[PDB]
Amino acid sequence: PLHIPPLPCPFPSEINEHADAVDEESHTWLAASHMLKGADTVEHFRRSKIGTLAARTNPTVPRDSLRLINDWYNWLFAFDDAGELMGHRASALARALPPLLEILDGRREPDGSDAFGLALKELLHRISDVASPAQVDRWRTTVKEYLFAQIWEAANREVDLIPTPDDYVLMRRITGATYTCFALIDVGGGYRLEAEEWHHPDVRTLSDLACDLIGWDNDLLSYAKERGNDKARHNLVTVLATHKSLTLQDALLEVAQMHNDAVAAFLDRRAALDRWATLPVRKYVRGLEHWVRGHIAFSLGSARYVGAWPDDTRWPRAV
Ligand SMILES: [Mg+2]
Ligand SMILES: [Mg+2]
Image (cartoon, rainbow, N blue to C red):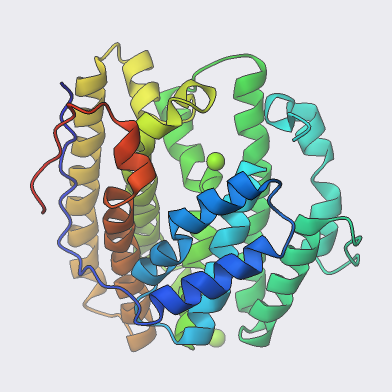
């Protein structure tokens, strides 16, 4: 039987007080968007409690901010899930991006037939209502990078390759859209990091470590579920097992070791940041901590993730 390694994390684990009410509001918004095809998928999303992830990763923000962030998570989950099999055609996916970039740049009104485009325009305008032009463009840049990164996944599927560790660790930071969520921490909190605060090497280093932790933790806990989706090709467990000739168990343990090394590096760099940080930088870094820890709590507690593992699988003690 397999044993799931613990993912120890000293960061506080909290949940927004508006979690259940906003989850319901946001799911209703997604169900009415027409972004999902089929009552079956709509019901799967409802049971997934995406608002729980939003509330655990943004536990301090006001109700209106949580609703905006929850709608954005629902857009991302829907976009990832959904058609023309463009996930296996790099050329076709690349050629399908310009119309979406036009909408993101505010250069074209979406067509009434374009569920993803209509919802993206709506979210851009709602973010613009509570964010400066510099904050809007910081988010827009992370979304463009996420969209371009989808072509890289399609490229791997097209030639049936499992990506190498180095290529995967770099690209996994942008394929998962986590940076698009980090870009809304100051916005959701009602504050604004200055350009030189945001781009300070210490803030970028902590942001990159948090983004690694979230991607690797998600890859490990979703692994059993992801085996039913393109043989979990885009998953650090598959990548390490394949390229380092490991057993599934030793691959799981190496992901947990990478997690522990990343946590140590985060604590080390945060001590250096604690010397100079302004209140907004300190709130942003606490935001990164809540995101990493809240994501673990959500993923550990997911019926769909836990259920996919074989019945004899051993889960670690609560850390
Ligand atoms: Mg994906
Ligand atoms: Mg300035």
